[PDB]
Structures are given as structure tokens and as C-alpha cells.
Image (cartoon, coloured by chain):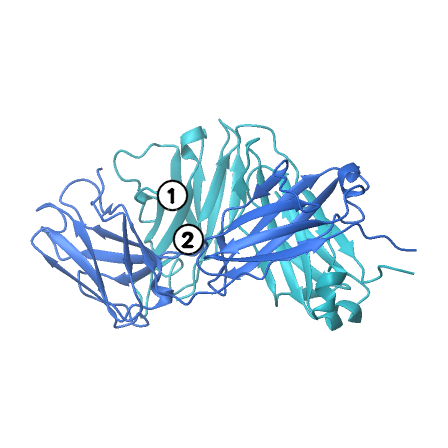
Chain colours: A blue, B cyan
Amino acid sequence: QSALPQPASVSGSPGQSITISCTGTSSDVGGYDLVSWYQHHPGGAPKLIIYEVTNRPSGVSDRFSGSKSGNTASLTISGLQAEDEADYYCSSYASGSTPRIFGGGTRLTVLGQPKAAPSVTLFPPSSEELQANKATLVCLISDFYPGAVTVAWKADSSPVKAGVETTTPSKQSNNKYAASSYLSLTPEQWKSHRSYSCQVTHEGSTVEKTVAPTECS
Amino acid sequence: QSALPQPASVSGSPGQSITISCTGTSSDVGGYDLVSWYQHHPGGAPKLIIYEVTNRPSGVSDRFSGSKSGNTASLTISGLQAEDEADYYCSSYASGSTPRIFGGGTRLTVLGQPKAAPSVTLFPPSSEELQANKATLVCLISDFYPGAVTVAWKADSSPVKAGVETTTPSKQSNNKYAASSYLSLTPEQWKSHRSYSCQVTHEGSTVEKTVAPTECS
């Protein structure tokens, strides 16, 4: 059955208030008082936050409330908090054969959250990695907001992008983002050049950390 | 409410059958014959495929079926096909504050190529980083399929969770996945132990990589 149309996404700021709509028809949202809403943080389990149009399970913040008018239902969130950032869905009892149809979901981004520069950390090819005749440098970028980051490499004060590989900013528990830039090199080209560096640029600023061939007894 | 735990990840090949479980209590799964299963493709709307434990709404193939025994419910998909690949959730009616509790979901992977065991590489704290009174270990996981892994860290045969951040696996060019996990530590904790080890599990198979403070003798 065709889903209940919902805004693909919405954005707000801490303390603000947002409304997410769920468009139904006289056969569902508008035919009964059985509309539910779910909050779902990807990776986690969906959570029932509203049922029977306006019922809010105990344990669910009063900042959330639901309602409907005609064939459209809405979920309103007040005093937006960073933790409200998640996906939200609606569903309704239907007059057809389907016992319950669902909305297509709405991703709610909570902006305004504090900014922060990344704490890049450069690693030299490990001992074992060198065994398999391999050598890769790791530029660990962590605790930064937004997930906006651009990285470059220098081979003895000379830009070299032959072997660069950066990951897509994965979010973390501390809510800040993290990513790693790899430089798949040769145990040959590493034990040759003097020192490799990593230049991470986050929101205008730019940080650098260099590492050179390490050897011991 | 506490999520009804279900397997994080399961895989199957075209034509085979797979079974996913949902664990609950006498207050929910056990207390009613109101278990549901939903199929959800990321980006799309959740689709109800099983309700009332074993009931199947119209339009839904006979390949899907549910059942329960005590406090554990189960979904079975037979004659697997590429399209069945998605996140699956269960839910049950419940007594108490919230009317319906949901499971954490299970990502099903219908094998479309041979499985690739993960290649793991562990990096020790750089001397440079150590100076700044910081200690970070990086664990790299590459070329694995299905794209799911769990990562754990140990200190001389003992668990660790503080400072443990692990990324989401991302699909690579070669159609296989990668991921990484780092562990923040104090140069003390580092030197304080004989060694730390990274444990990666893929499809039940677990491999380890260990590192020791000892750099020079």
C-alpha cells in the first residue's frame, strides 16, 4: 500500500519548535483516531511516542505531542534538544485490508550544536603491517563539529595525492564527528622520504601533524 | 521501555531460509498474541508483514511467517531473494506505560558474492602523540562482506569500554566494506599494561591483534 507522505527532512535549533506532518486520507488519518508516531535513532530500536492521535506513553517527554486536522496529522516538538535528532514516522489504522499503513519518515536534524575543531593524530606504518610488505599512514580526525573536513598530504614539503583515501564523517557518542584519512604507501616509498604530514582543514582553520621513519634497537 | 533484543545481523543465500528471533517477557511477547514484524529498507517506509504473531496481511508473500514460544517470537523468511535484503523489526503489545515495544532490528544480507573475512591491522601510540601525554590505539578492519562487524578491546585479558569509538562500516569500491575503531588512553594506562588487543568479529569468526608498549630495547 502506498505510504503516508511525510517531509523527507526538517531542521531546527535548540529551544526552537518543529512540526512534522503526515498526509493521509479519509480512509486512514482522517477516518479514525488511531494515528501513532515513532522516534527512531538509526542503529537503535523504534520508539512509540504517540498513539491514538494524542496519547503519549508515560516516559515520553511532554515536549512531544500529536494531533490531526482533517486528513493530516502532525507531530510537534518543543524546546528542541540535540537528542531529538532522529527519524520520525507516523502510521494509521486503515479502512482497507492493511491493518496499519506507515508514513515514509522524516529526518530531523538539530543544528546550532556547538562547534569544535578536530584533534588529528598521525600514525606511522605499524611493525606488522610492514611484514606483508605494506605500509599505511593513518590520520585520525576526531571530536569535531560540523562533519566538515578536508585533508591533504605532503611528501617532503610537496603535495602528493597518489594514494589518498578519506572516510565519510561518521557521527559519535559525544555527538561530534570523526573520520580517518589513509595514505596507502609502499614500504619502499616510506623508508625513503624523510617525513610525511597530514593537513586537516576544519571550518576555515588548518592543522598539521608530521611523522617520519622510526627505527630502534 | 527496554528494546526486545534481536540478532543484530544475519545472512542468507538466494533460495535458502533464515530465521530471526525476538526476545521478550510475560508482560509483552509472552503476555499476548500481538507480535508484529515490519520490513524496512533504509530511506523507505516501514512495511507491516506479520501481525498477531502468525497473521500475514494481504499482499505479503507466503515466504514470510511468524511464530512464538513463551517469551521468544520468530520470523522466518524462506526462498530468499535479493529484494528481501533489509532491516527487519519485531514488536509486541505490552502491559504498562507503553502499549507497544520494539526490537532493535536485524539487518538481513542476501549473499550476492563470496564472503570476505576481515583483514585487521592494529596501530600503537605514536611517540609524538605520547609526548603530548596522549595515548590512542587504532584498529583497522578492511575488505569484509557482509558489511557487519563488532569490535572489542582488551587489556591483558580484560574488557574495556571507556574511550572506545568505532565507526560504521562503509562500502568500498571493490564492493567490500571497511571500518575502524580507536581507543583513547592515558600514557599511564598504556605503559601500565603488558598489552592491549583489538578483537574483530565477522559472521561469528573472531580474530585478534595485539600491541605492547615496548618500542625500543
Chain under numbered label 2: A
In this view, B141 is above or below B15: below
- Quadrant hosting residue B55: top left
Whether residue B204 is visible: no
Q: In the displayed structure, does residue B142 sit left or right of residue A53?
A: right
Chain under numbered label 1: B
Secondary structure beneath disc 1?
Answer: loop
- Residue under the image location 35 percent in, 65 percent down: A112
In this view, A85 is above or below A135: below
The picture places residue A51, in percent across and down from the top left corner, at 22, 61
**Residue assigned mark 2:** A42
Q: Which residue type does callout 2 highlight?
A: Pro
Q: In the displayed structure, does residue A69 sit left or right of residue A102?
A: left
Q: Foreground: B160 or A150?
A: A150
Q: Which residue type does callout 1 highlight?
A: Pro
Quadrant position of the N terminus of chain B in the picture: bottom left
**Same chain for marks 2 and 1?**
no
Q: Foreground: A108 or A205?
A: A205
The picture places residue A103, in percent across and down from the top left corner, at 24, 47
Secondary structure beneath disc 2?
Answer: loop
- Residue under the image location 24 percent in, 69 percent down: A78
Residues at marks 2 and 1 touching, judged by CB atoms closer than 8 Å: yes
The picture places residue B94, in percent across and down from the top left corner, at 33, 63
**Residue assigned mark 1:** B42
